Structure formats: C-alpha cells, structure tokens
Image (cartoon, rainbow, N blue to C red; front, side, top):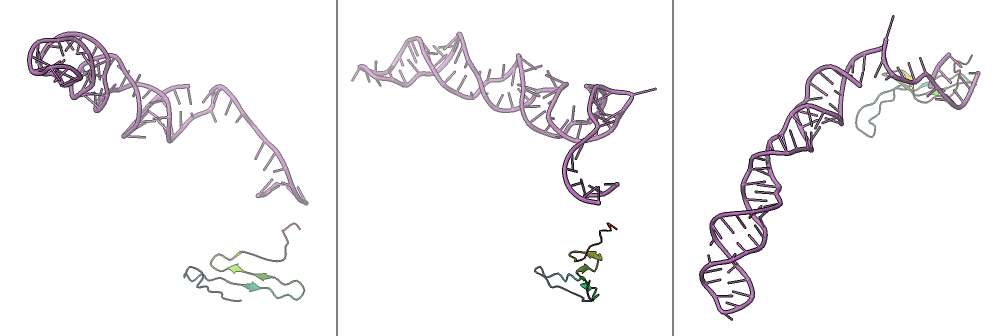
Length: 50
RNA sequence: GCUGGAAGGUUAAGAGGAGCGCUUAGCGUAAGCGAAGGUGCGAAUUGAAGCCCCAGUAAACGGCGGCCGUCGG
C-alpha cells in the first residue's frame, strides 16, 4: 500500500491508494482511488472475457 | 394532435391623438415667418382570442435505430 495523499494543484488533500500487486512475472501497479476503490489506470486484463 | 397551464414575447380592429404636412389671415423690403381655423398624415400608450413556451396523453396521430467487440459497449 502507498497512501498517496496529494496537496495537488488545488490544495485539497486528495488521498488514494496505489496498490501494487507485486506478483513477480504478472504484477500490476494500480492507482486505486481509496475513497471509491476504483481503478483509474491499470496494467493486466481479464475482461472477464474468460 | 388533443386536454390543461401559459409567468412572459408577439399579435388585431379599435380608443388614440404626441407630433408632421398643406391652406392662409397677419407680420412681412425681399427672403421668409406665420396665429387661428380647416384639411391630410399621424407616433406614444392600451389592445382579447390566438401562436411562441411548459406539462399530461399511444385501444391518439404515429414511431419501434445504427456501428465496435465477444451477449456487452
């Protein structure tokens, strides 16, 4: 977990998670918006096409 | 389309009657001004229904889609 606060370009203290599922080969750096727990940019898919 | 509302816009004829002309006494050296009256044109303001507008209505009119992916977007 990385508790990314941000005194961002506004001044508001926008807090989120940045979960990195370190899993060797197929890991995934995931900026998880903490208050919503929503992905905002991720790496590996499973659409769930299967 | 109908039913309803319709704050508001716009909308008549009509009441209008600000003013604008012309005639012409009189004033006028001329130039012209010109009162009154007449006569003609007349704006402002007001002017409903209505349509503009907002609802509701499909056993009203009427209408009942496309593109990408592999059923979803």
